[PDB]
Image (cartoon, helix red, strand yellow):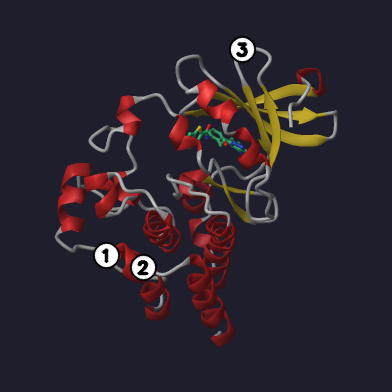
Amino acid sequence: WEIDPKDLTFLKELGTGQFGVVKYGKWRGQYDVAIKMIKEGSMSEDEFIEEAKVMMNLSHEKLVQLYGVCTKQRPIFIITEYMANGCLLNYLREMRHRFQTQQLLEMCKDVCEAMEYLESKQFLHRDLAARNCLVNDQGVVKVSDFGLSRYVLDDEYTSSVGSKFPVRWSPPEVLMYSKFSSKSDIWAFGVLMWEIYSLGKMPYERFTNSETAEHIAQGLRLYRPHLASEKVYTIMYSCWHEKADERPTFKILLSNILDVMDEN
Ligand SMILES: CN1CCn2nc(Nc3cc(-c4cccc(NC(=O)c5cc6ccccc6s5)c4CCO)n[nH]c3=O)cc2C1
């Protein structure tokens, strides 16, 4: 899906990410979109365009929808489904005192549904976290920026000892051997559940990344947030098995989440 940049209208600056400036605009004067303007040197562009077809085939309600790309010009554009309430982490922090427990679980469910679908397509996110989930005007959470980490050119982000690497969302096998799998996405999802139920707190606060790597290797895990039931915590904790093959699938996690709902 190559978009014609003439069909795009820029309206507002939405901020900055790993690829640079992100803008809000419209496609053909009607559809609200987000447009990532890829800073030169920030992306492995050839490698991205080479593997763009598969991202185009990924479609799910709880996945942020890709509209298309603009590659006949520089900077490259990536155009996506706009989400009015922005990223989940700040949404949690900003609406912290308004959340009911049922809502926190529905958020987990939204995300898990998306990841189950990705799991089914053998597609990895690689940087799952609240900051890379977005929220729309009706409070629906959707998974964002799935797979883009592979294309980042920044040693501080690509290196496990880098300052931007998602250490706090990474299992031991990633920090040690850089072995990404479904089960690394699983681990990350548990940390995400923790972000949700803690209402936007930073994992392992006052720990450095290295200290965090040290302690999870030694078996330390994130404490149960006040608003998390024991049933809920058991779900997120199951994502943090030292051994990846003892970790559940997203299909199972979703069943767990549904069972907790049903009981309530
Ligand atoms: C008043 N509020 C201001 C902030 N805000 N943001 C909104 N909604 C969106 C933000 C982004 C956005 C903004 C800044 C940075 C990033 N993130 C990135 O640019 C990147 C994230 C990652 C993750 C891994 C690897 C590479 C990248 S690039 C995004 C998500 C773009 O997909 N994208 N799409 C939206 O709908 C809505 C609001 C209303």
Q: Secondary structure at mark 3?
A: loop
Q: Residue drawn at (64%, 56%), measured in percent from left and top?
A: 140
Which residue corresponds to mark 3?
A: 74
Residue 6 image position (x, y, % from top left): 80, 17
Instruction: Report how many numbered discs are placed on residues in the image.
Output: 3
Which residue corresponds to mark 1?
A: 243
Residue 168 in sight here: yes
| Residue type at the position of mark 1 | Lys
Which residue corresponds to mark 2?
A: 247
Give whichever of 119, 139 is nearer the camera: 119
Q: Residue drawn at (34%, 32%), measured in percent from left and top?
A: 158
Give whichever of 141, 69 is nearer the camera: 69
Determine crowd level at label 1: few under 14, some 14-19, many 20+ residues with C-alpha closer than 10 A: few
Q: Residue drawn at (55%, 62%), measured in percent from left and top?
A: 116
- What label sits on residue 234 in the rendered view? none
Residue 115 image position (x, y, % from top left): 54, 58
| Mark positioned earlier in the residue sequence (3 or 1) | 3
